Amino acid sequence: PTVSDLECKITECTYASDFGGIATVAYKSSKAGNCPIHSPSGVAVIKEN
Amino acid sequence: RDKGAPLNDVAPFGCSIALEPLRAENCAVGSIPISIDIPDAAFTRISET
Image 1 (cartoon, rainbow over the protein chains, first blue to last red):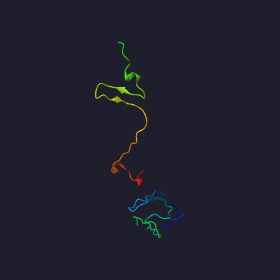
Image 2 (image 1 turned 135 degrees about the horizontal axis):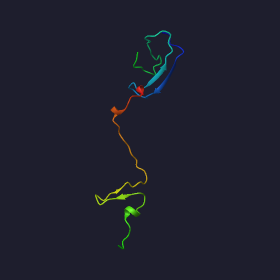
Image 3 (image 1 turned 90 degrees about the vertical axis):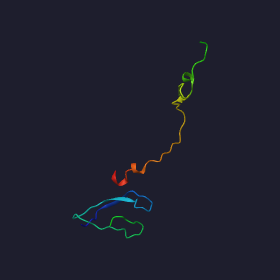
Image 4 (image 1 turned 120 degrees about the vertical axis):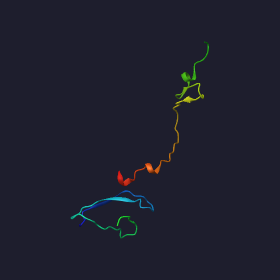
């Protein structure tokens, strides 16, 4: 699925080591299925691939 | 019969009395710096509310 026309926002970001940072994402898909994710910036490390 | 009145009838700042451990119950005055360590198990993680 193409996911654009979305929105992302943190909801409780934890300024920390353990994966405490969270963020809802208003996904706006075309199909329905899986969608691999990553932050190309090294600022954020994500638990979910 | 020529006494004075009782401290549970003349005290200030709101107290009651007992001939018991000599407490002065329920004295409403000032503030108390209270601090608690909650059980972390009782917390709900942020991504569930």
